[PDB]
Length: 70
DNA sequence: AAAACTATGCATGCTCTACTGCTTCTGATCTAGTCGACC
Image (cartoon, rainbow, N blue to C red; front, side, top):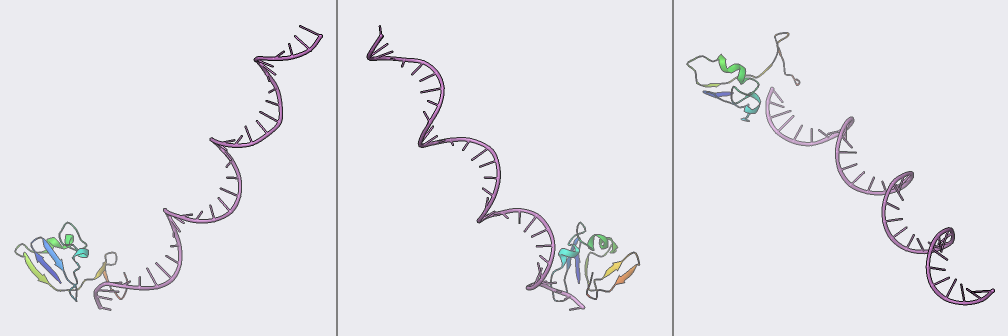
């Protein structure tokens, strides 16, 4: 689950553990935020979202199911 | 011609400085195992 306020991002797991270190707390750093920051529309500054985090292979353009690996 | 003084060489001990071999300490590497958290 992702919390967004302006340029500030925060991520939480199923049981409540912080994961912002991995996914980035600002567009300058991270593994997802620098690329998803510009996806949001002009009028949206505060947001809470819930979803799944997955691994994507661009070569085959396919989701790699995280059975137990990668 | 005989006796006293001195020079030089050599033996002797002790002290000091390189080289080889044994023992111990450190670093580097690999292998095995543990823990967080997800599902």
